[PDB]
Image: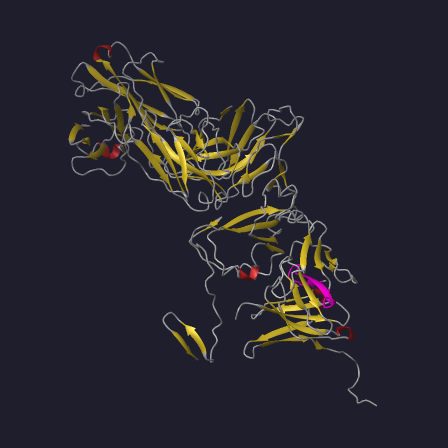
Amino acid sequence: NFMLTQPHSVSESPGKTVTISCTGSSGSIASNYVQWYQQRPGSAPTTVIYEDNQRPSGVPDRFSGSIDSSSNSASLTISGLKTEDEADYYCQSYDSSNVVFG
Amino acid sequence: VQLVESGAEVKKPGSSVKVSCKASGGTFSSYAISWVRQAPGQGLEWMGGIIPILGIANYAQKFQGRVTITADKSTSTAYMELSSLRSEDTAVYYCARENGYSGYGAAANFDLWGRGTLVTVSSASTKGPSVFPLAPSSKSTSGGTAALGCLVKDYFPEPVTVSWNSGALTSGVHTFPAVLQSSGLYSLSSVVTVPSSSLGTQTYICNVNHKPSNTKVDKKVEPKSCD
Amino acid sequence: SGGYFWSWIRQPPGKGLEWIGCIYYSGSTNYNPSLKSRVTISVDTSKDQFSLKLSSVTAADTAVYYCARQLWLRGRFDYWGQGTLVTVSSASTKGPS
Amino acid sequence: SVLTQPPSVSGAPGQRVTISCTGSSSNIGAGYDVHWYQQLPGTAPKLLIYGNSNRPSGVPDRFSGSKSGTSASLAITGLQAEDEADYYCQSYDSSLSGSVFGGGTKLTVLGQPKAAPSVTLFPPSSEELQANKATLVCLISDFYPGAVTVAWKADSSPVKAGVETTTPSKQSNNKYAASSYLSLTPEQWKSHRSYSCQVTHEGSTVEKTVAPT
Amino acid sequence: KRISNCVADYSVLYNSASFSTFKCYGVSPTKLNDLCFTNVYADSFVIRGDEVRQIAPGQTGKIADYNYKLPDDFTGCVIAWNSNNLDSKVGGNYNYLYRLFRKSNLKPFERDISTEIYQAGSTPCNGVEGFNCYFPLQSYGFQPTNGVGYQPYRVVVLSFELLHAPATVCGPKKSTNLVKNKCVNFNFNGLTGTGV
């Protein structure tokens, strides 16, 4: 019964800094690895962060993630918003042998 | 401080042995108390340690659930109860103490030790002792001195003291140690050399005392007539 | 070869991603509790492919199915296949007027 | 078990005597400390040194403890008149989930010169014949050291049943005394012609015979 | 636990599909086998469900500061799972202990087994259950009928050693699939031959 809570609508003007949260209900957010996926409309999702702080080769440095384990919330910080950044963001978990998305 | 245990104790193979560890003074309710056993013929092994202030039992994986340790803080005395005694339990326990410290190692050390409870279990248990006097002969005595004494047989358990004329004879006395038998029994002797001039005037009697058996039998000795 | 996993992930139009189940090259399988007792996935190494079978499909099962490679069982789906469109409707295929 | 120690070591009164203790990588190799104890035969063991870095009260500074990685070593300087005891290794074992002691090293070489033994044979008395047993005792006294083997014979064949030998104790004049018994029955005691005990001490053999009839 | 003169794989220790939690910083989980270190230290202990959160580099609390301090340059992995059906029993399982009070901070990778009574004020107690002092060691509250936040969890730590020394442990080439009936190059102990 572990579900990740995400803000449905987030808007920000280009060039500023915005924070996207991902709150876990029952399980703690530092228990399992959290993966963020940025999916274009009409396109396959792509992994933009892994291990909750490590950026895969290819994505910009701005995709920075932080973990606030006291509030059981996973945070993804975006700096310098651009045109191509307009995409769906989903946070991933594992719980216990049952992968749960955001 | 000074921790004192009990003395020797002999039980049955299949009975329950109850021993106690006594602490004189204080510093017993603030440190963990363990038990260390030493066995002649092998090394030392550690059963487990008991924290007395909170009461948590912490034994070892090499020992199964047969021996239990209970501690009382009203009189600062810990009690040990062991059941199903086997043939390889003939050893001595000790009352140890744990004094923790800080460091990279953090190893448990036993700075304080007890005296020792001699717990031995075997067959051929406590029966009625038999005393046999020994008399000299005309062929074994050639000089001015003769060897004579008393023989103790079929006695259990150790120890047994031997007194000569209620302690009136001390010169030339000797007590021999015991020895294991195939049936699990001990035997000891005492021989005193006296001049032959006092044989016909002063009589000798052996006093055999047995404090666990609560028996005190005295038998006189008489010289042989034919030899 | 390589000791990696396979997983099926679906996404309804306008909704978030939903995890269906994951498979190994052996018979190890784990399914979502909401999708339990309905997901049947098998691996045929001879054809170098794996297939998923679904039972009792309703009109709410309309989602874009994504076959994504999964490197770490608790981690990222590094490679995502292109999503095929699945539509569930109750009629016979008929020509337009 | 997991700790192995040498059976005995040799030394001289005035040189350095060292010991080596080798175990495993999970009890002493992990980083735990050692505690060395002295097992005197007749009194309770006490604490000598803990952690190989501090000196407990009442312990002389001649004892030194070191941990050369996996193996731990203890070195002393000079052999005094109290080193006739046993040394043990004590360390916490993670596999055993508790403390385990070592094997033990005895520190002694010699100190027992020779002497001239004297034996005595005493036949059983009259009252011992009605108890359906026969305790044949052959006493050995005034000898040094206390290492005497006892052999029994009935002038026709050695007796290999019922033989016993007690450990010898210290006498008042710093000598040794011992006894040896033999369990027989009165039924066959009178059948044999004679009985005797045979002992050897550095090539010196003394034989004493008795006649029941 | 110290592992030396051995060699092993971490793939078996991951595909169990039974660990509730998994945390490894410092190295990527999928690229740690081929990277080779010298020694591996295994630190195994038990902890409650509300204290697995505090076991992370850079967090405070009452367990991560009084029992085991995690340094900033912590490159180990933490593997934890639930085994409440064996280490707990009805009637109250109090066999596990933990420390609640300490005089000051402690160095990382250091164990404390001091049973001395912690002093809060300036008056000595001479080791009694008197005033202005309390025992630092407290028993747990494990119960088989607990929820998901207070059961006994088994937490282990697998740190790595990096020094001027050879690798006691290493990640050797795995058992590649034995592909057949294809033109594939192989090297079976004496030759680098290509063929079906």
Image spot of residue E178 (x, y percent): 47, 73
Q: Residue C71, can we see it?
A: yes
Q: Splitting the image into 4 quarters, where does residue D139 fall?
A: top left
Image spot of residue C28 (x, y percent): 59, 67
> Who is closer to the viewer here, A31 or B84?
A31
| Quarter of the picture holding the C terminus of chain A | bottom right
The residue that appears at 47% across and 29% down in the rendered structure is B113
The residue that appears at 47% across and 28% down in the rendered structure is B114
Image spot of residue E188 (x, y percent): 40, 71
> Who is closer to the viewer here, D58 or B114?
D58
Which SS does the magenta portion mostly show?
loop
Residue B186: within the magenta? Answer: no
Q: Can you say whether B149 is above or below E139 in the image?
A: above
- Which span is picked out in magenta? A82-101
Residue B208 is left or right of residue E183, and the answer is: left
Q: Splitting the image into 4 quarters, where does residue A91 fall?
A: bottom right
> Who is closer to the viewer here, B56 or B65?
B56
Q: Can you say whether A40 is above or below E156 in the image?
A: below
Q: How is the image coloured?
A: secondary structure
